Length: 30
Length: 30
Ligand code: NA
Ligand code: NA
Ligand code: NA
Ligand code: NA
Picture 1 (cartoon, rainbow over the protein chains, first blue to last red):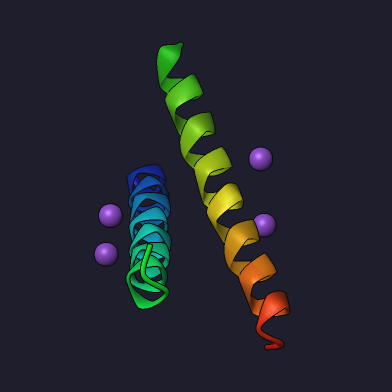
Picture 2 (cartoon, rainbow over the protein chains, first blue to last red; picture 1 turned 120 degrees about the horizontal axis):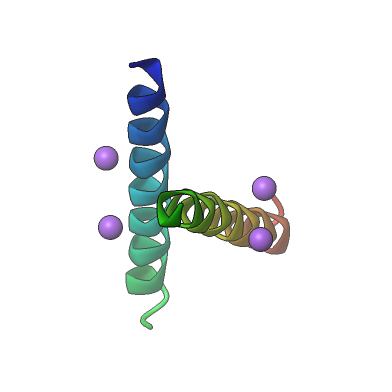
């Protein structure tokens, strides 16, 4: 179902955001 | 169902992350 795809998009989006925040933390030494 | 709560937690988490990234962008003038 297309509902599964939207849940997968949310999961992917949260991973991308978490990984961005992680990279920023490593940049500013945190 | 508890499934609804977990989907709500994901949505909330993505909003919190998006808002953090937005605040960081405003800080560094972007
Ligand atoms: Na990903
Ligand atoms: Na992650
Ligand atoms: Na929120
Ligand atoms: Na938002």
